[PDB]
Image (tube, rainbow, N blue to C red):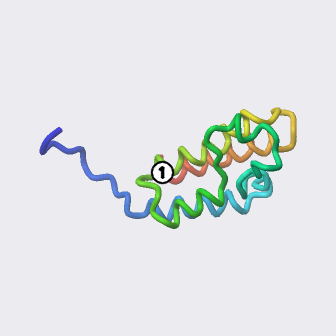
Amino acid sequence: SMSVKKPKRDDSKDLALCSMILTEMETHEDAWPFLLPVNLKLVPGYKKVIKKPMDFSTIREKLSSGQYPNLETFALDVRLVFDNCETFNEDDSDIGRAGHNMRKYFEKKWTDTFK
């Protein structure tokens, strides 16, 4: 509350570390469904169904341009990528599986880096 603060968690490396995580996600072999925005002209249904499209290139631009106020907003966009993927793809598809794998991979890096 006013003039009463919890001790200051050092957040000065968060930017760099989210960048590193993002790089590792970008370079994973199962990243391919997620590298670019889904083409909303060419994928029937996507536009109407997926209210908040997200992909790694868009996360990378937001990161590079100071559009994440903190590391939680960054993690929310990453997760959104996988949540969207699950909404639109069968678990038993290559993309569906990619998404489960990438999420698992992300969450581990996240925990190891920050928790």
Give x and y (percent) for residue 71.
46, 52
* Residue 67 located left or right of residue 82: left
In the rendered image, the vertical position of residue 37 relative to residue 47, given as above or below: below
* Residue 106 located left or right of residue 71: right
Q: Quadrant of residue 44?
A: top right
Residue farthest along the right direction in this orientation:
93
Give x and y (percent) for residue 63.
52, 61
Residue plotted at (70% across, 34% down) = 49
**Residue 111 visible in the snapshot:** no
- Residue highlighted by disc 1: 114
Along the line of sight, the residue nearer the viewer: 38 or 33 = 38
Give x and y (percent) for residue 89.
80, 36
Residue plotted at (80% across, 57% down) = 29
**Residue 43 visible in the snapshot:** yes
* Residue 74 located left or right of residue 108: left
Residue plotted at (41% across, 54% down) = 69
Please name the amino acid that badge 1 sits on: Phe
Helix, strand or loop at disc 1? helix
Give x and y (percent) for residue 95.
82, 44
Residue farthest along the left direction in this orientation:
3
Along the line of sight, the residue nearer the viewer: 20 or 87 = 87
Query: Dot 1 surroundings within 10 Å: few (below 14), some, or many (20 or more)?
Result: few
